[PDB]
Image 1 (cartoon, protein in one colour):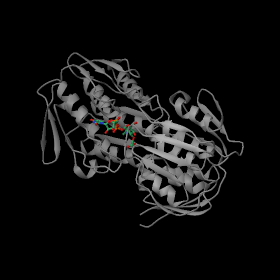
Image 2 (tube, helix red, strand yellow):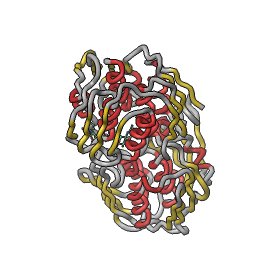
Image 3 (tube, helix red, strand yellow):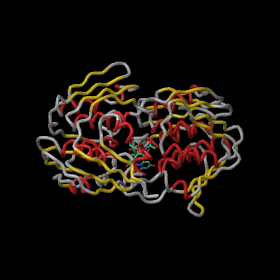
Length: 419
Ligand SMILES: C=C(O[C@H]1[C@H](O)[C@@H](CO)O[C@H](OP(=O)(O)OP(=O)(O)OC[C@H]2O[C@@H](n3ccc(=O)[nH]c3=O)[C@H](O)[C@@H]2O)[C@@H]1NC(C)=O)C(=O)O
């Protein structure tokens, strides 16, 4: 089992080129199940989640090739199920459900089980599909959807703001008879990206990026070429890496407008930030960060995917920082790991109260979250001594060659193979 050996402290300096969004590439890859013609998805990151998605697609009879792009040919889909073993390694597998029933009249996906970060049911996905006319049953742990003929457009109001259910409903709606309105839709940049992808295929969608999405169903979707937007979380993670190390970095292939909350919080922490059309620069001028207060919430508020990273920032900042999580209530596993490295903090309900320290110390820590756990690697970069991060497969699922990118910034990091 892979592990990272990080030697600190290091001041991160240099350039990093941002990869395509894991979170846009995923739903777009699933939506390609709707395409009758070949599709080329550009700017797809090289990471474990993409591997699992490619595997799932192949299991359905989809022809898949990849490099920077992923080429998809779904003209011969011949299988309609996502098995337990696959869903267990990637909850997003649920996204195969909607496209399958919308195009083929049937789809089966293993029902996701428990997860360490909190309760993550998929009730809204199921509810949405039902509203569209699909019949759904649970058999042997498999959510089985079906419809005789086309789905039917419906006016659906969402009980929660949900990135995943908004994608499920939006995607399936593109082939339904009539008009579908998704009220209280998630507004994430990835939702806009997926909608734009659909439209490039011939779908009729408007309102993407707002709380109300309208879809007018069409008979078929064709093919085309589409470039995935930049990864906002990868960008935020690198920006934080510089901000906590007294460093200076420039992020290339970036999309500043997807990061307003994070940028503003970085400025509050004392960062000198400049932005261009496709770039973001950050200079700490060798200063320790100032503690900030953060509240996660749906886009365009501060994202839960940046939460652990900012918790780290607060932990080495001057002052008492407070972080409140409103999306994933139990997403605090990183805290006790950081405390093993010398940090000080208390968790009260969904809020962590941080007491910044001057320096962290190297220690053995454990990764458990595909986005949050990158925080441990960052911590290792600025801590005194050697930090060993176990179970880095988690990080591999969410970041493209993070050690390579960090190394190019001056980090002392080694991938240690257990085999
Ligand atoms: C952790 C990841 O990123 C996450 C990111 O943290 C969240 C929030 O921004 O949005 C995506 O998850 P998601 O689609 O499961 O999350 P959402 O559906 O918005 O969930 C928001 C809240 O609603 C709840 N929820 C969601 C769907 C549903 O049917 N029922 C329900 O109760 C969740 O339990 C959570 O409390 C990302 N995943 C992907 C593949 O796009 C990851 O990379 O795997």
